[PDB]
Image (cartoon, coloured by chain):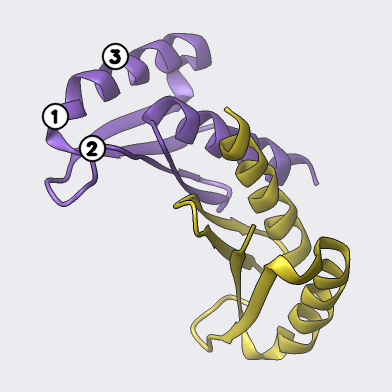
Chain colours: A yellow, B purple
Amino acid sequence: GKVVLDAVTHPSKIEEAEKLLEEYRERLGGGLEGRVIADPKADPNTGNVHLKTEDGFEVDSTGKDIKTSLDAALAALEWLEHH
Amino acid sequence: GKVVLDAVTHPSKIEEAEKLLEEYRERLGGGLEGRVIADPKADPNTGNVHLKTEDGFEVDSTGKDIKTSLDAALAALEWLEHH
């Protein structure tokens, strides 16, 4: 299904976040609609990802980098989609 | 460690949310500090849980009931605490 993903990042890490979104786009296919939000108030030392499905599931996940945040967020989404 | 948990629920489901927080308190011990937020704008058909550790990990999880939301939220927290 469609999953709308937002990577919210300090502007120094926009490149990082885009390259990561690129790997997950080509693994997860065309359902993944991801975008990078450039937030100067964001801590460069943390990652933050928000995802929303058209089914109404939502996860916000704040970790120490963007990749871990995302993986944890998809982990939680897999749980909700099954249980 | 300390985990601050918020169950945000329509006021009709406050009892449900408190009894659920009670089971997770006695399973997860005294580190779990959970509270019920009574939100009349919340859909009674969904669950929502937010957790925050003193380490800075945060997860917000919206599902179709409070138990699934919570389990998914702790699932994501376990991922962040390891990876």
Q: How many marks?
A: 3
Task: Please report whichever mark, 3 or 2, sits nearer to the chain's N-terminal start.
Answer: 3
**Residue linked to disc 1:** B12
Work out how far the residue at label 3 is from the one at label 2, CA to CA, in angstroms.
16 Å
Task: Please report whichever mark, 1 or 3, sits nearer to the chain's N-terminal start.
Answer: 1
Task: Please report whichever mark, 1 or 2, sits nearer to the chain's N-terminal start.
Answer: 1
Check if mark 1's residue and mark 3's residue have beta carbons within 8 Å.
no
- Are the residues under marks 1 and 2 on the same chain? yes
Residue at mark 3: chain = B
Determine which quarter of the picture holds residue A75.
top right
- Are the residues under marks 3 and 2 on the same chain? yes
Q: Is residue B25 above or below residue B74?
A: above
Label annotation for residue B44: 2
Return the x and y of residue A50 as percentages of the image width and height.
55, 63
Residue at mark 2: chain = B
Return the x and y of residue A64 as percentages of the image width and height.
69, 60
Return the x and y of residue B20 as percentages of the image width and height.
35, 18
Q: Residue at x 26, y 19 (%)?
A: B16
Q: Is residue B79 above or below residue B25?
A: below
Q: Residue at x 88, y 63 (%)?
A: A27
Q: Residue at x 47, y 25 (%)?
A: B31
Amino acid on which disc 1 is placed: Ser
Return the x and y of residue A24 as percentages of the image width and height.
82, 67
